[PDB]
Amino acid sequence: MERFLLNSTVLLYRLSTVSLDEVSLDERVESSVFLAQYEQARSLPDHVAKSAWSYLVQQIKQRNMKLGPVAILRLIAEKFIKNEKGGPKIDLPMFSEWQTLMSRVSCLPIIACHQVFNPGPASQEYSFRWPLYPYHPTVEDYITRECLHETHQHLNGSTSAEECWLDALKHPEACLRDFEKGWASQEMKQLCAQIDPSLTPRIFKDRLQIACNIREILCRVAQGVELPEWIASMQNPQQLANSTILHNGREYGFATVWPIDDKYSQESEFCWLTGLLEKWRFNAPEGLERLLWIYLLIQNQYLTLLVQRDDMTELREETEKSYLSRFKHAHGAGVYSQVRYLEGRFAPKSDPNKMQKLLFSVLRGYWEYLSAHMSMEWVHEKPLTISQVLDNLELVEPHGKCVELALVPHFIKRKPKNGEAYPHALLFKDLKNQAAILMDMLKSEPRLTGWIRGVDAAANEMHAPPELFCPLFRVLAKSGIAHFTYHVGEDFPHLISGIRSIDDALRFLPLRNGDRLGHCTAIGITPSIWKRSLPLSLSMTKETRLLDLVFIWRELRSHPELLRYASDAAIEAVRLAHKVFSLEEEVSITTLDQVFEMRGLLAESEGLSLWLEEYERARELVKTTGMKRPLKLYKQWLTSDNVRKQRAEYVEVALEYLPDEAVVALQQAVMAKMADRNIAIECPPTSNTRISQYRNVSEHHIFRWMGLPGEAIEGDVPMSICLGSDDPGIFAADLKSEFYHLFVVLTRKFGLSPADALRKVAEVNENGRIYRFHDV
Amino acid sequence: SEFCWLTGLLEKWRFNAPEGLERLLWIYLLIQNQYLTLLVQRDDMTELREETEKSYLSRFKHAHGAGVYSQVRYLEGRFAPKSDPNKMQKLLFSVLRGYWEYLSAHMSMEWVHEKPLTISQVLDNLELVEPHGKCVELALVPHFIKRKPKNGEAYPHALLFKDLKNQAAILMDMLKSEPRLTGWIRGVDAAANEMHAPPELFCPLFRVLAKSGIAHFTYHVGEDFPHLISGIRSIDDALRFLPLRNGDRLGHCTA
Amino acid sequence: MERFLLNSTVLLYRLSTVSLDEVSLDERVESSVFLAQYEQARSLPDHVAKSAWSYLVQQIKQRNMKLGPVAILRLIAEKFIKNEKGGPKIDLPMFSEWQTLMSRVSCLPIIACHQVFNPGPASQEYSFRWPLYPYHPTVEDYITRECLHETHQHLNGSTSAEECWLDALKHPEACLRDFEKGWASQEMKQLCAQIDPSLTPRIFKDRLQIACNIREILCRVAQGVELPEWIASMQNPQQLANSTILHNGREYGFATVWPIDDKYSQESEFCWLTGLLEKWRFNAPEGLERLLWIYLLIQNQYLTLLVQRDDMTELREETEKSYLSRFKHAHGAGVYSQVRYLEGRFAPKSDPNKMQKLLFSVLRGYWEYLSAHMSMEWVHEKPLTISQVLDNLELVEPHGKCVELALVPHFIKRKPKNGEAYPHALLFKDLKNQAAILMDMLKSEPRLTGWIRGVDAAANEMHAPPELFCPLFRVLAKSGIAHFTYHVGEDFPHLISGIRSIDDALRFLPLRNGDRLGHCTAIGITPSIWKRSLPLSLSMTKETRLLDLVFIWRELRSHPELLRYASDAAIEAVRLAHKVFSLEEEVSITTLDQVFEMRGLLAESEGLSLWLEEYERARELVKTTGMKRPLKLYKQWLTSDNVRKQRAEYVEVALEYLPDEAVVALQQAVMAKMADRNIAIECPPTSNTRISQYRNVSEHHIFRWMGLPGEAIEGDVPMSICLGSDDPGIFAADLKSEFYHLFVVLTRKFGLSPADALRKVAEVNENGRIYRFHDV
């Protein structure tokens, strides 16, 4: 119940409109919390909710304390954070709920309260730079001897999600520019409405301006300096939404002296927060306390909006410090790094000059960290260009104990735009330029191929089918990239279709041995847990439906017991082929497989340098071999207006079209093909509840992949799974935090011994090293 | 010298030895063997003050073994805290001084102070040392001791606990004076017996040390329990009462 | 079927005599190939062979090429080699078949062909120095983590067999005189007639001279320069055996100046081949192309002869470059070595000055290898002597990243020379001379024992009894060698005899804990494979039979089920003993047991400084217990002319003398003895096709040791198994290939998971360093 007093939109609204002149808020805060609980956790019964709230009220009462943000922080601090060997750590039994709590509330206010109200032993120096971890000897030594490995680690943004809020305070005006740009589309309009339906761009600037000005006020309190005596002129928090105050009709700003030069840094915040709570150890004024409550509500609300929004001015905020800070953050505390092989996903750009700036800035950041850590003679003291960075980077020897980097651009997809005879045409011409821009950069300086080791495509699956990238990835292959990871988008309209998309990537795309497939939730989720909280009937596009049935018949024709579904799949598929292709003559199910087997051919080669070499590469195979009707259908399948009209139409598909065993049969059938190619699979963080079908982490599909007998199914051919922290869904995240999360749930929920619990997860961690993209 | 003296001596008596001289060597071995029999049996002032700093160096060399690389990587050598604050400070310096010179011969790198002669300069030389896995990592752990229960004073251990309360302050104030020693003073132990005092006696002593930055606590469960069922309860007392976190150790859990 | 089309003696003979004027050789190349297909592989049906030839021709017509190496190399290169991240890598499915091909055809033309037609991506530079390996991320990770461990690497010769061709070209007469001197032996006469009956010393010189002249004339074509017009007389290729053409009384020397300074390196030849094939992408002239076809034929013929022959000035042509190249090749194409603990065996030489230079040269080359890789201040810059090299190498610590070395001399033996109290007498004095030479050099420099660690005896088995090395090894033990390995020869007339030979080595030789054994094929092979294609009766010396029969009785008296064979052994032994010993008064089986137990005693000492110390030791132990019946018999068993004639007689023993389980019981008895003594088994290379009993590598006996179900019979005792790339049987050899060759079979031929297969071979690789002779 503590989270609902720190991250709640409705409670924020009521406090913001209440002036400070009256502090009769005991009933107002209570009623909003119940509503706030109602809009976050619907299923929680009311009788339990009222019972839990009453305990918290008396828990504050028996503490000779008043209800406030300081009061909430205290009960949270003594509940979750306990001092241990490495300073302040987290209780192992209570770590599962802590990760859920970080999905709603930031950790910096919480750590400040614990340090002030329960300091670390011997007053030893402690500065917050990493998220809190629970200490376990079994796993800690594994970190010491074998560093962690990270695969899906994006570079845009910052080290974590919280300090981006600090970067938001750096340029509040720039925040509107990016907020307005997204808000123009209706997709972001509903996304913001989901968190705050009463949200407008002007209101957003108010809260950002309100939060900054509250921070200035409370920083004055922490400084020990007397307030500027405009407190009598201040009664409404809304007065802080314009960065100006009046005193007898006089213009007075909010500027104040900071002994810490970088007032917009995480170090400044923790230093400010600790001093604030120390001065409020026994009693705090009601007026000042509510300002702290508002600031906490603003910070937790914006970050709640930010994590959803992530899945111009902000891009060019610093562009070099974040890259350096990321590697220092990824290194971890201590002399020796906790991460050995860390590969990054950087956003490609359509400007060749901007590309040179992007690669230089990140490579300069990588060299800066290595120079700071490893004192070793450098050819150039200041490289100032990519050529000289490679001169510095070619000197260093890989000894493992420092972070090894392998940049991998991630191609981005867009909505299927009509026209040009096939729905993904502006996409392909844009993607073709992006690849070509990287091509000339690589061929100009071949030494760059030691760091640009792979290519990724992580936007969606509905927006763009996998087979569109077959001409793209293969033409990258002739440039010496030699690694292609495909991040399948898990927004499948049907689970069978989701498995169908996985098979397309394997068969069509050039997933050579050693490559990876990220976010393979479809081939991981349990069919029994997918059906929950779903309507009796689903809906998906006819083209998806037709490709689904053909794919079903490809894997269900082999099974003797699961045969009646394949025969019915063939019967229904040809009937849809009659409706979709609008063909008059006879059509056979065998021809459908043959036609769709050709889908890996290029976009323009269906009508038939590196690209022109690839052009006739798939054109010759079409002409030489005998069949022509599959080409005629494939040509019709691509560039026929009626076919395009029919494909976009939606159809009604029963939820239980394939029974539980049959879906498992498909899920295991693709697994065998998955393991044959020896393709590793990136795993999203467990706390990332994007799918939202998992009510608790204990039923996450990663447990079934690892082979836990409580969750594994018969016929499950083992896979190889690698970890990754890409879209955590929580404000304070790190790989080591996720590593502990895997260990805690296995130790507590499953009862596995600590020695064995590490062993099962160590296999997952080491697989990132087995299938690394870094050169030997 | 003893080995060199004996090897040359045994060569001279390869075929025969004079009867009187041979018996003297026989007598010498019995005296040495009997003394060593008593010495190791004592456990179950001037002895350690011959040089008090060179013997600690010799311990690491013996622990290191032959070859360039030591066969033991981690080594936490327990030592007895001293009731004199100055004497303990000199005792702690000698162990660290002996440790650094062992690194000096083994390592090949610069030193901040060529002649440390004090704990402050030793720590400066020691912080520059990075353990690469071949040398011996050292972590001093003072181990306490007990005696028979002191009759009276409202409970059996009030005069005994007073010395332990003093000894912790002897360790603590020096630790507070030089907080840089936290990385080498890591654990606290108490290895005398069980009948001397129950394990819960150290609960206040461990908690104050824990909150003052020791960060580790090992307890030596002595195996002199009057009955086997009694010995199990002594282990239960340590677990239920002592503040043992996840990563603490127990010695001789034979019971 | 391309193997027969690039290595076939009859085709090369027919191409040599037939002039360059004919263009249609299909009527003869087809007849020659089918004939050559017979003798090389006489186990293929004619119709299948006939169909394969037609398909090969039909595939050429598909690519409208002309029948020749440019056509043949294209098909082979595209079928096997695939471009990958590290360059050209063999396909995993085709690796097993590739290794069989490698035993007969060099990969240098194949890799050169692939580089020309489908080169490396992004114009990345590919330097051809190492043989191709298949790429698997699982195995690659482990080998980079824990480097490969090698045990049996012969220092003599160059890195691989391919450049011994290059040396042979560089030494037209030195390799001729080595062949000419070896031609006198009748054994070499049979071997040379085996590969080709028309092989005479003159014929050998003609073909080498032909290859030298063909290489130069094609080099001129490769460089682009026009031909020097002497081709007017170029009709019969046989003219190329005179080093000078005749054209209007003009002497034309075929030698031309190469652009590269050295004309006898792999890079020199590979770059030449790429230039040659590049100009012949479309078509080639028949006269020049046939010259290339001819050139490949002598190369393939001689390389097949060289590797089969293994069943001086040339060795010491450089004596510092060859070993450095050997160390460089063993290091691998990387900064850190692929092979950590490499044991370089070398042949000891009786001449002190000759071998003193050799020992310094290999140490200097090893030191030169470390200096090139690792840089620091050395004790001396130009050692020029054995003492300064050792002082230089004392500074280098074992770091693992480079190659660690430990020389182990392997004694070479001769045929048994009758006389002087024992049949191997002139040998023993030569070996005693060799040991004394080795001992005094250890006195010259005590540090030599740091690198001189083991002693080996690898020539054969039937010639030298294993007990003969008891006095040789023991004196070396007191000399501070501190390790010994015995390499039993696999020429055992009977499988039971092979078991006895390993038993004799364990009993008598001072093989203490940690010592190794080599080529222990006798115990590994199952009886079913051994009897394949053997005659129903086998012949062996009466000396061997008596030793085996008593051995059978010693290890079968315990087993209740196979008890009659133990009794049959005793009765047959005493019956045979009366024939051999020619004794009137009967001899018990127990008396025979003690007679053969005294085989360890020195023959000279039994007939009666360190040599006299051991001489009296055998005499002393004899007189401690007064048996006086066996000792008198043993004296007769060694120094009786009538007995020595009887022991040399051959006796016919049935092939199935003992049942399959009886041999199994005998084997597991030895498997028990190796467990107690903890003796390793450095297995010979898996591609070494010399046992000729396995129809494929799938039936290699090593898998029985590994414990795979379906190959490990019940009752077997686990061993410790090392690896050695000593006698690969293939052209381009490395331990890296062997590790992948084993990995492929378990993953593919045995259906094991990649995680499982790596673990089993990791246990084998680890044993290569658990029992390594390198000092701690």
Image: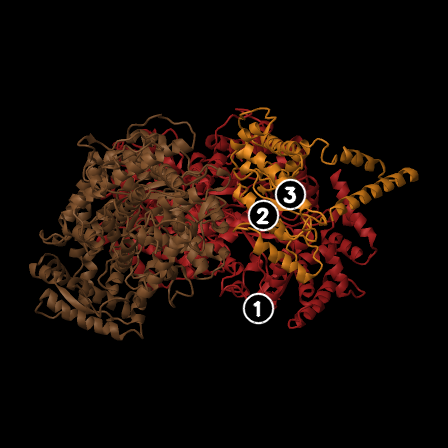
Chain colours: A brown, B orange, C red
Q: CA distance from mark 2 to mark 1?
A: 75 Å
Indicate which disc, 2 or 3, sits on the residue closer to the N terminus: 3
* Residue A204 x %, y %: 20, 44
Q: In this rendering, is residue A323 above or below A536? A: above
Tell me the number on the disc at residue C660: 1
Locate the C terminus of chain C and report the quarter of the image it occupies: top right
Q: Amino acid at mark 2?
A: Pro
Relative to the observer, which residue lies in front, A695 or C624? A695
Q: Which residue is mark 2?
A: B204
Q: Secondary structure at mark 1?
A: helix
Q: Is residue C522 visible?
A: yes
* Residue C722 x %, y %: 54, 50
Task: Indicate which label's residue lies in the foreground, 3 or 1.
Answer: 3
Q: Secondary structure at mark 3?
A: helix
Task: Report if the CB atoms under discs 2 and 3 are less than 8 Å apart.
Answer: no
Tell me the number on the disc at residue C542: none
Q: CA distance from mark 3 to mark 1?
A: 77 Å
Subunit that carries the residue with mark 3: B
Q: CA distance from mark 2 to mark 3?
A: 11 Å
Q: Amino acid at mark 3?
A: Leu
